[PDB]
Image (cartoon, rainbow, N blue to C red):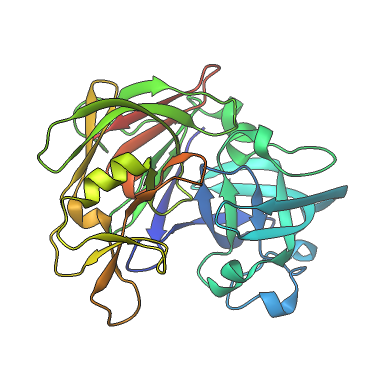
Length: 330
């Protein structure tokens, strides 16, 4: 089997991407944030504290003939950005882009933190990291991909995120028309439960490539590119007036600037992030200070190849017995 679904930016900055997902019988379609940095499929629901729902579409398990309470199971997750959610668990039928999993754990939120409430466009998350990170207790649950894998034509999914435009998540096949040149594959460590890999270096604009190993994660659920302070300083030093602002919480730059590209290495291959992808616009409405899309990972504890990086590539998440990651230009 295969599936193919369009993913759409939630706003004009590509802050996140939503993908329609069918849950239950008859189908309830919710728009979920596909997150290769976590491993819980959780939704706003009829059980979510009413004051914490503001515009989201909810899953109502009592209206699904295929929903079953997973008795005794609870979940609770805290994300790197300080947001969180928790609740109980149902199993139900879940379909993405025509690919159907029966008995998928659907984690129903009883509570969500303010950042989730405030984002009316995101009805929940669909985790695509390794199932070892799943938070369901006392019986850990599998991700949608893990459940689907054996039925897939090939044990892969691909992320093809758009810049200020829709893109695609495919399951079970590699669309050879969706990228240019060849796909370069690179080793993955699953030791921390992430799609963790090592970039071979970087360049800033038309500058020379610096060969250096940068361990990090491929994370569709993080907006920006978070890299070591040395690398980030070298990038922003090429933008007149750019500076790190403790008050704003990262690097800002004059909105009048033209940003240089940023290149990262995948083996001997190179992925080029155009400068425009690194512009996240005014820090506040009407400001002439703009927020940068490359930020320091210092004190996150991990480097994160988030959407800024991933949307410059066609990315293969290869879930074979020994997982790997593939990157192609597009």
